[PDB]
Image (tube, helix red, strand yellow):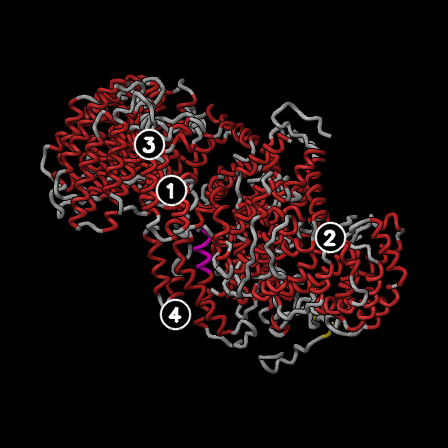
Amino acid sequence: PGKQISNTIKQLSNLPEEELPTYLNNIYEWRCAKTDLLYWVDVLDRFDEILKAVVTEYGLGQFQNKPMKESDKEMVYAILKFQKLLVENSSNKSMFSSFDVVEPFIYSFELDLAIEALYLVSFFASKIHIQRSIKTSMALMKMETLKTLIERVKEKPQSMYTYYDETTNNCKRVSIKKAVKKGIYQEIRRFIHAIRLHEMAEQHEKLKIIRMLAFSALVYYNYTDLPIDSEFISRDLPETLAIINTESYQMREAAVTMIDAIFRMRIRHSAVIAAMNAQSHEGMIMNLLKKVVNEDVPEHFAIVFFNFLSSCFASGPCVSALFSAGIVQYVCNTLRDQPDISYRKRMRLVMGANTFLFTLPAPFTWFISENGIRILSKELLLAVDVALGNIKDHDLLMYINSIMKIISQLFKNAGTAEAMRGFLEGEFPRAISLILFHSEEFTPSILAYLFSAVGDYIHNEPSNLPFIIEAGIFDGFVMCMKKELPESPDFLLELPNLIEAFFLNSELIKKIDEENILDRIFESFEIVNLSNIILMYDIGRAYGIFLENLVRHYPIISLTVKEKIYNTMKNLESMIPNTDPELMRLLLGNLFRMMHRAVYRKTTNNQLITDKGLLNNRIISMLMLIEIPTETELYTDVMNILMEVFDEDQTYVISYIAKVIDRVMKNKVTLENIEKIKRILLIVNYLIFKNEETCEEFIKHCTSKGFLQIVKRISQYFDNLKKDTALVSVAKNESLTNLYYSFTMGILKTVYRYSKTNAKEYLKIFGLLVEDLLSKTEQIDHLYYTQRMHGLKNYIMVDKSPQQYPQKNEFVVTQEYLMGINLSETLMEHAKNSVSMLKDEKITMDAHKKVVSSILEVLSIYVRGIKNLFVPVKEPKKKVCEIEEHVLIIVELLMDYIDKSSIEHLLNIVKTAFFVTLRKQITKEMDRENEGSAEYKRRNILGSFFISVFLNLPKEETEAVLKSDIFTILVKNKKTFKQVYNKNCFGLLQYAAIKESRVFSHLVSFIPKMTKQVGASTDPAFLKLYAVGLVFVAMRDTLKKTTVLSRFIGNIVFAESTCPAVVEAQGIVILAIVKLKIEYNLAITIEDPIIHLNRIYAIVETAEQKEGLVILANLLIRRVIESKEAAKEAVDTIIKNKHLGKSRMYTVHTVCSNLRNALFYSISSFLEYLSSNFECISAGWEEIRHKIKIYSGLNAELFRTLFVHRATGKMEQIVRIHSLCLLVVSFPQLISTLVPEDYSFFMYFLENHAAYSKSLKPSAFQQEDKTLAYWSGHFIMLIFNHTTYVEVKKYILEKVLELLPTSINATVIFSELIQEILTMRFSKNTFDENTALVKEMNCLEVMIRSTMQIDNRRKDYGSIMEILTKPMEYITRILAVDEKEAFYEEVTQQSSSEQSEKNEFLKSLCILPISKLIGKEMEIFNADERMPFVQKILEGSIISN
């Protein structure tokens, strides 16, 4: 911002609309630096909205108010002109959203509005070729609307106007000469424009310049993807240059802007130069230059024209042509010949120069050869000698700025080193000395470019340096620096460069040391006003690099630089506590980011300027004063430099921080001191954590008595902080205790993880800290026990075995460390005392649960690595048996207080008590003999207690651990078997039953007792248990037992239910019973399942997750249909699927897992297949040598009976037809035996299929309607594809042909029916007979008859035609082609939640192959079991066979 910026913003925002033009007219030109548009957002919005109000008052559609007020027009005219004036010197113009209002001003009746708005448009879209981002801003209006102004305006050019319109497609006139009423005299706007051009001819020159402005604006939006031919440049460019050369100024303004637009896009610059006459010395732009220097031109047009020239000077060939014309000699002649030209003319000349003296090197070479530099010296000296003794002339100082810059970039460019020859010889030294001696009254840019050029020339050669020196140049420099320095960025940016350039000589170094100019260089940081500039630019990095290179090349002043810089850090640290916090935050950020690169580098002489002790003193003094956020860059830099210093020498750093923290500790207790200790604890935590490798001395000092006494005093002070809550709140006390404990944890982890840590020395400090902790525990206030006990848990955590070996959970050496402390006695004391308070009822029950869970986990993970725990081992059972006795005592003491937070730890305890057994570390014989053991009976009675405790909870909590391997042995006892069977928690029963065999040994005996309770049990768990038990006993009896299955006789009847779980249970029971009956002789007889089937279909409507219901229904129905031979052949095909792969498959287990469905389907079939056609399975003994459907026993009558079911509801009919599709796909042979009369029922299928049109989508539809239509059509087309049945196909093709021409939708859907009939090809020969049958009936005749008969004049008629193009074309292509290639041809040659989930479920439904159907249906029976005893015993049977 600034002073004028905000003042103009507020004036344009507050001044009334009547007074707005009055103040606007004062500011004729922007005499200020380039700004940004983001500050005038409010001004832009106000001007835009008042423009909307004005134009809406005018109508924006008809311009009804032709006689308009002068106040509003003057207001808008000034608003536009000065908005433009503000905006040419602005930034970020892609956000300009006021563009949409200017279009009606172009067509407005007052053409001052139009000229101003089009001037704004010209400026805004003149930058398209450079920025290219104004596409969004200027896309508010079309680029095609204003094309009515291609025609040239003459003296009343046209009294005839022709307009072109649609539909009529004719051109005619509308009278304009009437002009009776102002209302009627892109199309009414075009009519208004016609009236403007014809009726009002007095202001015909004005509308003429309007038309040029509008055509130019169209060019500016887009110069159009352009018809660029040779003739385009041949007429457009010469006509425009003649326009500029001959006619007036307003229109040549648009002309020069548009030719600049044409130039900048950089196309056809060869023809542009050729027609441009730019290579001639007197080209048209140089002709304009002569005109401008001779006769005055308006400032706006002059600025635009010279910006056009500057754009021209950017391109290569263009500047080459201009230089060949002699632009350098031209401007040199104009400069030499007359001194009376204005400063602005030479300003424009040198702004051109700052481009064409750097675009190409040849103009620079000729300029050097043309004595140009000395001419510049002459003009500069005369300008400055006129300057002296007079008031501030803005134009003169801007000219001097321009001279300084042009010389600065001329010297800086590497290829422009030709100017070094004539600097000293010319009056450049005198001019630069004069500039230095009067720098106070000059623009700071003058001085910055001066310093830049001086430094560059000094660096160019040291030959002429003294001639600079004793000429008083350095004297003038020093006396200039003595006065208060300018507050400019570039001045202090370029000062170090000249300092180094002077340092190129030793005498200058000794003199600057004598005069100490570095004082100001260093002090440049601590200025509040300049601090903003320091924020903006990267001054700190520049200072750091400068000082680094200075000390690198010149270590002579290293001592002085060091002393002065440390004095500067001390001075800056002095003003920290007594200034606004953000000020030190940002100043310290700057100072640290500059010392980051200034000090601690790897170059030479940096070790001289890196002092560890003093820098540590200053950094610690900084640290104990200010709080620093983590995410700030200053935090990162201070951490980086401090860790580098610490890594340089850890010992002195830790010793010094220790003594400083002790000394500040012994002072008064203050909250600021609390912040200091907090931050010091945090920083020591980070430095401990970041330490990758540690020296042994650091570990020893951490174990030194001084360090531990410091830490114990810290603990004492923290306890003092715990004295009162008002000073340190409970949250603050908890936080400080947590951070202190975290420090202890970190140091303990570091010392333990240290290589070959001294066990005794580490245990010494560990014992000291734990005894301090337990001493602090006896205090009555136990509210902080949570973090203390978490701390002791972490103490257990740090002393743990590395467990590097995978699948290893056992203490390596930490067991002895743990047992050497007698922690068990402390556990006993804590347990009894906690139960004592439990009797005292002063603790919340949930708090009691969390306390006992904490105790349980402490004990569990304290003992889980104890060796030979519950192991009957002879020698080491002296104390581990005592530990087990303690554990049983404690668990007896806490028999009634096991919570969900404790059940996992109880599982951990039981896992530890049986670790080797469940990990199969037993030999099945050592376990078989270890029954008579003290540890064995102990763990038995404990397991009894755990079962008793677990059975005291509701089902919800027990569901978490319903599947644990511990129960496999817990229920293995028949006593516990029946005890938990009485508890009715059968999920454990199924899981352990799958995982264990003796549980089945008892369960099969149990089954006959509960065979009677099955009837209408209405329980999921009981029924699934019955099913799984029956199937498992059936397979076990097939495994050469047999006689057990024969003894089971009974019968069960079922009732009706509405709850789903009951119906899935009944369905699974039917599955099991029918599958067992069809395969094996079982005396249990059940009724006809079809009643339960229609139950399922009647109920699937309301139930959720119908996927299970439908899949079980389909599987059971094919079980009913299928026979043993069909299943055996299907299993054979499944085996052959892998058999043809001939992979390696060395292990039996992987093959069994991949084919679990084949194994568990019918074990007899797979066993006989492996006996005869054995696969390529190594079988654990070398390698083995390796190597149309007709089915019987089917139930076709049931299919026929369900065929005429004719249900009513939507979803169950959809399910039934899906089942029909699946069964016919699986079993096409059943359709062959249907009654020859049922074909009349296909009417329903084809009708409800054709009722809905998927192509012509009707609204108010349901997704279920789409599903029904798709599936109904799919069923019949599947009959076509998958069946070789001719007569039924002939009958149905008849029916479809008669029903086709009934209606338009019927015709479309029937043509699509035939299309999908012919598209996907089931088989080659079958497709051939299909084609023969379809051609025999000659469908084409009648269907094309329907094609042209229904032709009617209607809106959707045409759309129906392109819909129907594809079917006949495809049929004709197929039919005409012979049988051989016809098969080879192709085409084109929470209510919402339930609805969404059921729709997605319907979408998921599709046809699947039988094998994965088996897999997913019997996943329920296997319960996704991986390695049961079933697979092991089957592998044994296979191996033995």
Residue 1204 or 86: which is nearer the viewer? Answer: 1204
Could you tell me residue 105's position as x and y percent? 53, 66
On the image, the x and y values in percent for residue 639 come to 30, 31
Q: Considering the numbered disc 4 on the image, is that residue within a helix, a strand or a loop? A: loop
- Tell me, yes or no, whether the two marked residues, 2 and 4, touch with CB atoms within 8 Å: no
Residue at horizontal 85 percent and vertical 54 percent from the top:
1374
The residue sitting at the bottom extreme is: 180
Res 1055 seen here: yes
Q: Nearer the viewer, mark 3 or mark 4?
A: 3
Quickly name the residue at label 4: 18
Marker disc for residue 1193: 2
Contact? badges 2 and 1 (CB < 8 Å): no
Kindly identify which residue carries mark 3: 864
Indicate left or right for 1222 with 1016 as reference.
right
Q: What span is in magenta? A: 81-89
Q: 650 above or below 168?
A: above
